[PDB]
Image (cartoon, helix red, strand yellow):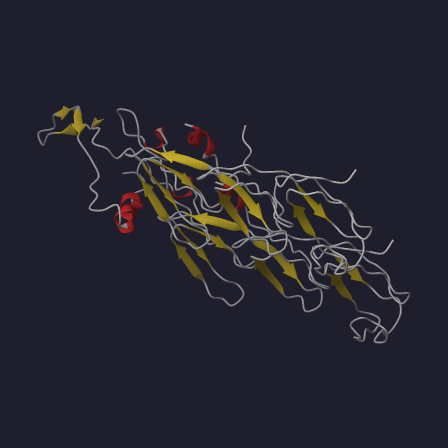
Length: 174
Length: 224
């Protein structure tokens, strides 16, 4: 059956054979050794010169929330948020991870989606950028969305009648 | 049988075949790979070029009450309230959820319908927007309907003869005159310890319902 498909659906199409600039709907040249995604509310059939790869699907999203991506080629990684967004021909989900900052963050998860943390208006937190090296801060009643490389600057509050620094931890500053 | 159907009923219609701009009642073009809902007090039969999908039905509603929706495409989410409203061709119910704020809210549920909370006239609550980042406040004898992303700013009241902050929780702020008792020990300069039972009359002033900033003062304290 012809691959009729919704715009939400997508198909990467690796080619076993060299250029297809002719008789393609896009007329675009396509050398072997690299290929492309196809999507849109339309029917499609594989050409003899090209093979189907995978059924990447819609990745629904709303504002101030999203998922990480990274190019296989250049290797650059970035978060993306807001509009619904499928991986393109090369981008892939990337696994962000934390140095035991997660359980406090909660106070099972697909880490590939961008991590975020609601900040109480009294609270404030630090994020020391390791990319542009531009550390920055939030202060107010709003959620915060990390760049994947930007680790939190967690603080170790003192606690108890004796003031022991190790006694408690809280990323937020009340 | 022909799909005769009430306006309340609806049918999404995915097409297996390309454009149907011809001989359609709407004359509208319809490329394959994306499709549309059909509804209205009318009979309908599927075309050979298109297949039936699902029987989405009426979603009855009244004023100041409704349900969440989100586009599969743009991914934008919004509450809708008031008039009865079926999901369109792409919109779908979305699952709002809370950080254990629910049981207090009650003081089993389909979370996809918009959550709401009646507010007693003495009571007031905060909602710190995470979308437009426009935090806002209610104060009066009226129900409140959240934007799905707008979490409550729950407060942790102190309780007991000792004043322990962790002891109680209440999203509402009963800011009326109702005096609260307090017990604080003290000692005289001559080293004579003594206990005290001391009531506190109290109330929050409000120059205007109109000014958000005074409410920002009301919520500025973690625990007044």
